Length: 32
Image: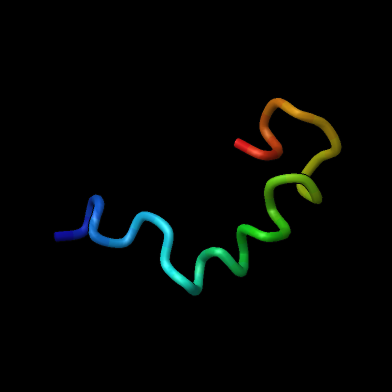
C-alpha cells in the first residue's frame, strides 16, 4: 500500500532533519 508502508523512510529523514526547526524557530509547528 501507500499509506503506512513508508511513513518515515531513510530518504525523508534527510529532508526532515532540517525542516522541523529551521523552517521556523520555536516549538509549535517546528518539531511537529
